[PDB]
Image (cartoon, rainbow over all chains, first blue to last red; front, side, top):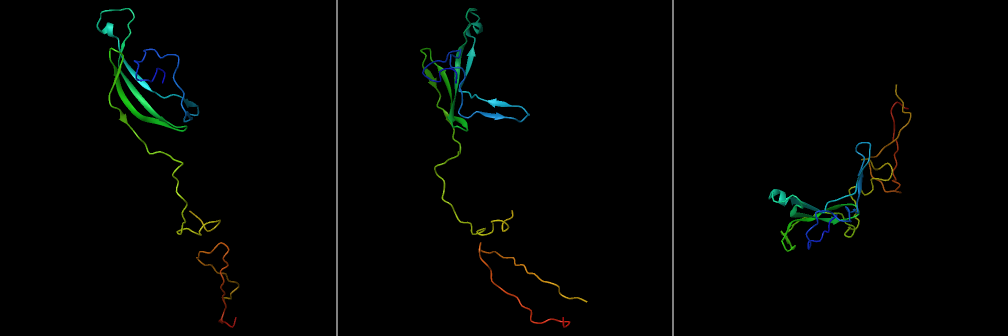
Length: 135
Length: 34
């Protein structure tokens, strides 16, 4: 999430002043008797070819061009995040993005809106409350 | 020889929370002239 996630710009090879972003849902692990804390997620991955080296035509200022940008596009919630989508992208000599049609995801997910009303339990209906339950 | 000292009963049942099941037992007669 460091470089400008807008598609209407070729990413810079360097990142800019953003740094990598935060997240709504940082987790931590202790599976070793020691902490891990997990603050980051991707947004984009970029492929670079050192053109004038590969051409073997120049040696100063070897800026590789971006051949293509992967987009890694996420759904966010305060406890979880996951990909909504991904795309192949590449950039024209005029700087326009050109894009593949995305691949898109969805996941069965928690909710608080839809909850059903309560139901009686004939099968058990009295067999609890101190001694009458055991299980 | 054998003589009865005491008795108790148990019923595999379901009962309402505050349901006081009502029943009773009685002895008609006994051997050995007790």
